[PDB]
Image (cartoon, coloured by chain):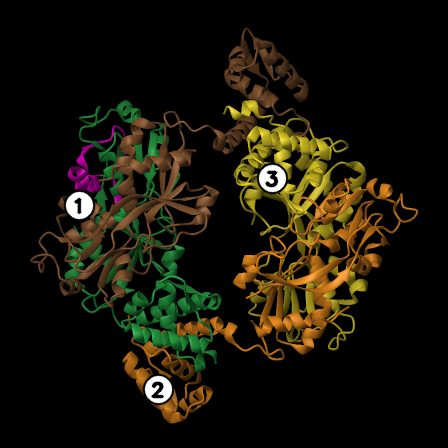
Chain colours: A yellow, B orange, C green, D brown
Amino acid sequence: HPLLRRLDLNLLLVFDALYRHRNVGTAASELAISASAFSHALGRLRQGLDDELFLRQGNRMQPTQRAEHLAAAVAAALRALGEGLEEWRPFVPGQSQRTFVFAATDYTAFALLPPLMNRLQHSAPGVRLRLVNAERKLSVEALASGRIDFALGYDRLPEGIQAHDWFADRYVVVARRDHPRLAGAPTLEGYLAERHAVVTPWNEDSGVIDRLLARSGLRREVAVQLPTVLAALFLAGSTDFLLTAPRHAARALAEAAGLALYPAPFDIPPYVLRLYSHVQHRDAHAWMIGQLKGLDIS
Amino acid sequence: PLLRRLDLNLLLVFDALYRHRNVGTAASELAISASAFSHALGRLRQGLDDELFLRQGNRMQPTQRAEHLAAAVAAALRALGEGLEEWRPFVPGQSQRTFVFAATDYTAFALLPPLMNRLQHSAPGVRLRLVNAERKLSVEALASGRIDFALGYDEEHERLPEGIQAHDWFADRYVVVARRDHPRLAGAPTLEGYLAERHAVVTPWNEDSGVIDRLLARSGLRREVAVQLPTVLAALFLAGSTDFLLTAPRHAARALAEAAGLALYPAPFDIPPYVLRLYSHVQGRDAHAWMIGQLKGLD
Amino acid sequence: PLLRRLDLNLLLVFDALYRHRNVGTAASELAISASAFSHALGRLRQGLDDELFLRQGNRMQPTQRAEHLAAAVAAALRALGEGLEEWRPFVPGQSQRTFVFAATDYTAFALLPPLMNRLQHSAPGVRLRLVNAERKLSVEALASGRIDFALGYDEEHERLPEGIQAHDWFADRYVVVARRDHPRLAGAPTLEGYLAERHAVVTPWNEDSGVIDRLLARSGLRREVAVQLPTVLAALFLAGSTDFLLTAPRHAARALAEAAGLALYPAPFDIPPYVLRLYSHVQRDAHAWMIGQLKGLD
Amino acid sequence: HPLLRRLDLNLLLVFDALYRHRNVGTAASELAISASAFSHALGRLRQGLDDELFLRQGNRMQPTQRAEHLAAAVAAALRALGEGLEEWRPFVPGQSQRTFVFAATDYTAFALLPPLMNRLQHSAPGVRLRLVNAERKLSVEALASGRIDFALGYDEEHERLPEGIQAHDWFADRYVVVARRDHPRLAGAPTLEGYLAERHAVVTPWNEDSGVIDRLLARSGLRREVAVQLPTVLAALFLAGSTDFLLTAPRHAARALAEAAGLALYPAPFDIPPYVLRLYSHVQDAHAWMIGQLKGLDIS
């Protein structure tokens, strides 16, 4: 191309940050340059490309058509380059300003981050994490393209994917403290007589407990499905609904939500929280996997 | 081709009779006389050119063809009935309907406990399904009726899109949350003290910045971000195990202050108060007016 | 109740209007007059207290409520349809069945003329509907029974997926085609002659490359592609008015050789002769009858 | 990114040119920079990557093993950029290498490609075309994106254009009734009832439940008995030559196959508007040229 030779490729970072942030202030912050230098860089990109690229519309900077068409190409270019350069020298935790991106849910964020970041805030003070909601627990392509470094969840692995287990726990049945129909653990029949709250973190049709019960031809009555366990626990606290939840979350919220926790009157295998990654993926990744060790999760 | 010749109303007659195996009881379910039923039966026998059910006294036994047909009919009638549920008159105390809400963990935490404390007794068969959506307000999903309502609040007086209506239900403010014993906080943070810490940031739709970063940028300010995540309730547990500051809804912060070990402070800069709203598409229903009315019971 | 007050026959009117978006042709499919159809639609509008379809055309556009009912009604009629088809033994001289084939222009060209020449006499009531499908074999479609059969062949001795069977019905080979007066071919091209020209390529499922491209690559060769298009018969006329070479099935090329003005040559490289197959889900006498019909065909 | 933020990315074109040429004089002339400018840039990149990157043997520049890992990443990145920036390449017909993507049917591919490519093979010899079977005639979505440059078809009577879609006419033609040359019941052109007493082949290019003629005929209270629907006119014309079925088809296509498939062509015994085939595009250089190409194009 004759354009690559004329265009200051450093302006591509400006273009990419603004397309993602739609905001000059937060894009300039990501880039660690001043609002003024950012605005000047945008004027140059406008001149280099003979296009406005982004016009302010209230809050937001909105891309033109030419910008919209260029955006995936630039982000693909920067991904190839960044991966390229990461491989280049070994990972240095004390100096790293890298962001690790995890696909996660509220429960994995809750389980993982507080003890991980209690460490990282000291041993790696410039490393950042970014957790995102994903439409699936485990997208290989996202892991393969390096858009996402890790995925979190639990429970045979797709190809190119490995896991590192980092927490193991069990499910309990949760009800509010003064539930009218509990004077100990529900029986199977008593559990199946109530209405249930169910956590579906990827907007699945049934919960993990529903599918478990199906193996035995059992079905519960569902009052509410929601993606978030911590909110589910406050819901159980203010209603007569039962929630079958990770015990680690339920204990953390038992006093705040006013909850009682009970064994389930059917078997539920203990679960193990795991970190998924792509086999392709590397010093930064190994360092993070190694951090998941010294980790006492409560 | 043979479906168009068949009086499809007669399939209700087949279906009741296959289920009941007796004419008086099947007729009773359909609310017609036994005579009426017997005549419909004779019509169906002609329409399918089969005896369909063999009579022994008053026992009614399916022929081989009837048996083979029965699952097809039950499944068809199920599909029809499911598709017409949307036409069923809404009555609160009897409805078995689901309301689908696009939400975040925070609006789920804010809405569900009180709404369902009441709806569980007032409308014991109504279900709610909350989904993470890829943005706060997709007009198409709401126009579809693929989701019924969305929850969130208006940022910096954004204009409601094309044919969205909203109704306010909860006013609150943001506070600055730190772990209760923070190394550098002898008291409320100053602006400089706030900007000297790293921050936890809630990005409920995977945005690259938080609502507070964007507010700060409008004054030429920025904060050092250590973690972004979509969930406020986990974020408060994060603030409680680290030196990270979290600038969060006071309603969530108070409910977890003791569980997460937090201190709560006023922001050392101006933050508009926020109002949680319920958003919908302008295209009617008794169900929708009713849920809009239930969001008018505080906490 | 729900079903109980509604005249369920009115759901066929609904279904036909939803598919035809045209009162006249929807009425025709149902073998009723326009007025009956309109009175029936009036009864549905009442029964459902909607308007269901909006005359914005001379075409009929669904409302939002019709929009939802539509898939339910479709599913109901499909279920009934299947059960009723099992009902009586298949009688070819009496049948009014539509057989639905996934096909390409080439397989339609190859199959339909000799098949229908016979069926128009031996099964005057039987109708065929050929559809362009997303790929040759999206087996879900064959199981759903959305499609009775699919035509095509198996490339590179490929195995074909589980629960799918197939029956040979045409053997043919590939041939290199050029306009008769091409300035540099009046006999078979050498490989270098072949690879010096530009090429038309048939990609029937909008694929990235042609079967001959994939073949050539296996030997580390590349041809220069001028035109990709999904239609063999149109590609033949393209080759007749240009200096492009097309590598295409001989049966099609012979048919168009005079009309398009083409010369036909063997390829300077090895192309395995292909077989046109009939594909079906193992899962029906209607199906076995069709299988028996291609069977004994020329 | 955050190592990208640190690197002068423009130095990566010097890296990439030197990796391909393995000689500083030709890498430099590829980049249109002086020798000393090149050598300074290579010096900066060696400081930026803290590596030699290339060792000199004569004039031969041999990449360190490090440099080897990085070149593929640079090449991929530069390839993605160049492709997104093609949009900015000045359009020259005689030299252009672009691929135009059209949404089409077998009929419109047949009508357009022979004369279009008859010309373009000479006038724009590196220009390529890609025709795809789209799920409908006119998907404004695909046009906007520019995943598809153009769409081909005709307006049904006289259809209103969606917003952001413009159309340009390229061929006026009419429909005719086609039968096998020796049909047992046609002593000449069919009458209306003669036509309605046959079974019919019908072309439904987007898999619709009716033909454009069925729509038309129903508007006079008339219905035909359909034996076969298929999306291809050209296969349909052969079907008509091997059966008693009638087909109501574009004249341009039926004339091209009359001999090959053994057909007779007759005027329709009812009124059918002429059709006008058109080129559709979204309101948003290459596109302007292609639009002008069809303008004077001889189809017949």
Q: Give the numbered dot on residue B40.
A: 2
Q: Determine which quarter of the picture holds residue D204.
A: bottom left
Amino acid at the residue labelled 1? Arg
Of residues B243 and A10, the one drawn nearer to the viewer in this rendering: A10
Q: For label 2, count other residues whose C-alpha is less than 10 Å away and answer few (under 14), some (14-19) or many (20+).
A: some
Of residues C258 and D114, the one drawn nearer to the viewer in this rendering: D114
Q: Is residue A295 visible?
A: no
Q: Cα distance, mark 3 to mark 2? A: 70 Å
Residue furthest to the right? B186
Residue visible at 31% across and 59% down in the picture: C148
For the N terminus of chain D, the image quarter is top right
Magenta residues, start to end? C250-276
Of residues A83 and D158, the one drawn nearer to the viewer in this rendering: D158
Amino acid at the residue labelled 2? Ala
Q: Give the numbered dot on residue A54.
A: 3
Residue furthest to the left? D187
The chain letter under disc 2 is B
Mark 3 and 1 residues: CB-CB less than 8 Å, in contact? no
Do circles 3 and 2 both sit on a common chain? no
Q: Determine which quarter of the picture holds residue A144.
A: top right
The chain letter under disc 1 is D
**Residue under label 1:** D255
Q: Closer to us: mark 2 or mark 1? A: 1
Q: Cα distance, mark 3 to mark 1? A: 53 Å
Q: Closer to us: mark 3 or mark 2? A: 3
Residue furthest to the top? D58
